[PDB]
């Protein structure tokens, strides 16, 4: 029973982490904020000041 | 005109330093200067 429960839990994690909108927002926010900061630095290089 | 090499250009008053290559994109007939992004001259039309 313990082995079956562990195997089922691992399978459920694989199914839940394969719906294309799983809980990976904390990892995506870091890359998104770094890209936003870089793009904003470029866009403020565009200004004439 | 010497393409595929780094050169200072003064195209129609625009002074700058950089290498130019050959592109295959098509511009509109009414466009001469080109600032694709970030307030810099990506493209410019050679008057000749």
Image (tube, rainbow, N blue to C red):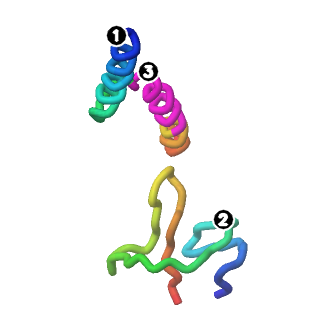
Q: Magenta residues? A: A24-38
Residue ID for mark 3? A26
Instruction: Determine the residue positioned at 51% across, 85% down.
Output: B47
Labels 1, 2: one chain: no
Residues behind callouts 3 and 1 on a single chain: yes
**x%, y% of residue B39?**
50, 52
The residue labelled by disc 1 is A1
- The reply to whether label 3 and label 2 mark residues of one chain is no
Dominant secondary structure, magenta = helix
Which residue is under mark 2?
B16
Farthest residue in the top direction?
Answer: A2
Query: Who comes first in sequence, dot 3 or dot 1?
Result: 1
Q: Are marks 3 and 2 in contact (CB under 8 Å)?
A: no
Q: Which mark is residue A17?
A: none
Camera-nearest label, 3 or 1: 1
- Between A48 and A38, the residue placed more toward the observer is A38
Q: Residue at x 50, y 73 (%)?
A: B44
Residue at 44 percent across and 29 percent down: it is A28
Mark 3 vs mark 2, foreground winner is 3
Question: Disc 1 vs disc 2: Cβ atoms closer than 8 Å?
Answer: no
Instruction: Provide the secondary structure element on which disc 1 rests.
Output: loop
């Amino acid at each position: 029973l313990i082995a079956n429960q562990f195997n089922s839990a691992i399978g459920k994690i694989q199914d839940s982490l394969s719906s294309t909108p799983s809980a990976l927002g904390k990892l995506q926010d870091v890359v998104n904020q770094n890209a936003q900061a870089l793009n904003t630095l470029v866009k403020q290089l565009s200004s004439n000041f | 005109l010497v393409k595929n090499k780094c050169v200072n250009f003064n195209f129609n008053g625009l002074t700058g330093t950089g290498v130019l290559t050959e592109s295959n994109k098509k511009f509109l007939p009414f466009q001469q200067f080109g600032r694709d992004i970030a307030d810099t001259t990506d493209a410019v039309r050679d008057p000749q």
